[PDB]
Amino acid sequence: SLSDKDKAAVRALWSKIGKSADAIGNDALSRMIVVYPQTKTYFSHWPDVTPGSPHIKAHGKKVMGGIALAVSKIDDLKTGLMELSEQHAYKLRVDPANFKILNHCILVVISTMFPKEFTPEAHVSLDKFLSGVALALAERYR
Amino acid sequence: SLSDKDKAAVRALWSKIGKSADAIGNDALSRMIVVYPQTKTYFSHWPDVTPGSPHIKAHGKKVMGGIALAVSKIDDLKTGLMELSEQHAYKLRVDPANFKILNHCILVVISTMFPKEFTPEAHVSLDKFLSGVALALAERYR
Amino acid sequence: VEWTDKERSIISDIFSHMDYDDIGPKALSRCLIVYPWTQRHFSGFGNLYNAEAIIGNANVAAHGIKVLHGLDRGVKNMDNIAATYADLSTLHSEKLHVDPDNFKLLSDCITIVLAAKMGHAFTAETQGAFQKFLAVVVSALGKQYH
Amino acid sequence: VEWTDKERSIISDIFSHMDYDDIGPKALSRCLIVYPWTQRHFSGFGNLYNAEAIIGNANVAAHGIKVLHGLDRGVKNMDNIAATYADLSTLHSEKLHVDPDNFKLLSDCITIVLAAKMGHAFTAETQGAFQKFLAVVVSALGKQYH
Ligand code: HEM
Ligand code: HEM
Ligand code: HEM
Ligand code: HEM
Ligand SMILES: [C-]#N
Ligand SMILES: [C-]#N
Ligand SMILES: [C-]#N
Ligand SMILES: [C-]#N
Image 1 (cartoon, each protein chain N blue to C red):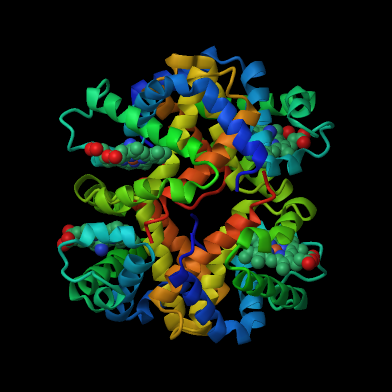
Image 2 (spheres, each protein chain N blue to C red):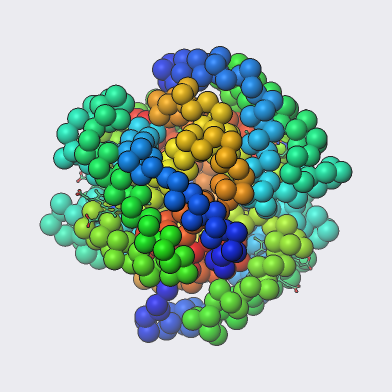
């Protein structure tokens, strides 16, 4: 679970990097689909899923808006992300094994874009937080 | 997270099988050390870690007493298992990757001993519960 | 894996005594209940509305029996498992879009169903050999990097 | 893995440009902070009391440099990785009692530290090749069944 120290660390990091949320999301989804090609099928209804796609860019804004929502809802991620859980489990049928994949890709992108801010201490709390986000997104699955 | 349905299911299963907790624990630890030999090192201070050991049998009582504690504390596993978390993280330094291993071995043993009671619906809630136990045991690690 | 003769004997003994028509349906229905997102691959099988329906579903049963017979090719040549399952791996990934994680979840359900049938004969050494065998098949199906 | 020529070129390029003395210490100290149970293997290295101490610890630095040089043998013969690391795997397991999960945690820290150094040059295709290579080494070290 997240301690007060973890919550403060995540909020301070997000304060620093959130200006670039849309770019982070575009890059993280772009990487997930290339490096973990089992994920591409969930986006295949879009007219373009190739590198540089405007559908990936648009969706990246939404994904990191989901992460911003989670930062805002960090004191109770289950309640905060319940609607997104239902969407991924029931409407979209995304296999929940994939949440940790996108979380790793978000960590890689933040490291590429904010190497100064993304210290080991920022990383431990953000990884705990993304684990909590994955668990909350898993809420409606079983 | 555990729903009211999950909590009721776990309590009803435990009501049925808890009479055999000590035997379940002996068999589950015995299997973990043989099938996942990376775990044996944590018990190697005991004079006997071989199949049939009385130290394994004694420790099995304690492990499943920890599971009984978790059943009793199912509404708030983090608070209920906090002391055991600290013991595993700080005094014993057990790598937290191993909690899911022992959890699988507990499921295998309950299936061998209570095939009638351990239905698929009992298994989904018990697996959710053991995931929650592992997360609570992970509380003091980072 | 460099199989020991004992491992080969244990795997041969288990599969010789296994009733595929009993174990296969129970393993897959158990997977569809414990890890219900896997139901997505079987939307065309008829009733999957609740646990009772899934356990009774004959299309699920036929498929679970298929899975177990699918393990036979591995049992018959335990030193060529990755190559033997290359085509099945391509089918489940390129045509069926099965997540590679799902193979491990079903294998654990097969182990738990076999443990229920074998009872105390499902010894730790039996479990070790059977899980090692399934792990090698799961790695071939999931196209794991090694 | 059947490596493509492009994968071989990307791995060779990355390791040719890598400053092991910078990346090695950062990867291991990052692992000891993000996954701090791994500190148990380095109790004799001196100060590991807080993040500042771990990052500055010269024994941690030397060890992280060792890890990266330990990847060189894999880079030099990418088609023989499992055999090449068999002895290192035995050392970490039978003598050091390193949990096999820990290899994957450190590899993710190496990837994240390399991503910070390379920045936008750490393209998705670069990440894919580098992670595939580390996955093959991690499987050899952890003695995964395949
Ligand atoms: C950090 C984890 C994730 C977060 C925060 C997240 C967030 C979101 C958000 C905010 C939406 C938009 C919901 C709406 O339409 O109102 C969405 C849609 C979606 N997500 Fe995720 N998601 C995550 C993980 C994943 C993963 C791992 C996958 C698949 C591999 C996935 C697949 C999808 C798909 C297919 C859609 C619908 C796109 C469309 O509208 O066509 N998500 N997600
Ligand atoms: C379901 C997960 C687990 C539960 C409920 C659990 C429960 C317990 C309990 C109740 C104790 C006794 C604490 C005391 O001394 O008061 C204990 C001790 C211990 N546990 Fe666990 N444990 C679990 C997982 C593990 C795992 C996965 C390992 C190692 C692979 C482990 C290794 C140990 C060791 C080495 C001890 C100390 C034995 C001694 O006294 O010499 N535990 N555990
Ligand atoms: C031990 C793991 C498994 C083995 C050995 C296995 C084996 C098989 C075999 C032998 C077939 C028949 C091929 C054919 O019809 O030509 C098949 C088909 C199929 N399998 Fe699997 N399978 C495994 C796991 C899975 C999992 C985990 C899923 C779903 C999550 C799955 C979904 C399917 C589907 C949807 C079909 C198509 C058959 C139809 O719809 O008629 N399989 N599998
Ligand atoms: C990519 C993964 C890794 C590689 C390639 C690797 C490589 C190495 C090498 C080359 C050595 C030196 C062998 C010798 O001194 O003869 C070594 C030693 C050692 N490694 Fe690793 N290692 C890896 C991961 C780990 C992890 C994850 C841990 C701890 C959790 C670890 C703990 C140690 C320890 C404690 C030593 C002993 C050296 C000493 O105390 O002087 N290694 N490793
Ligand atoms: C969601 N992507
Ligand atoms: C604890 N065993
Ligand atoms: C495949 N069933
Ligand atoms: C190894 N360090």
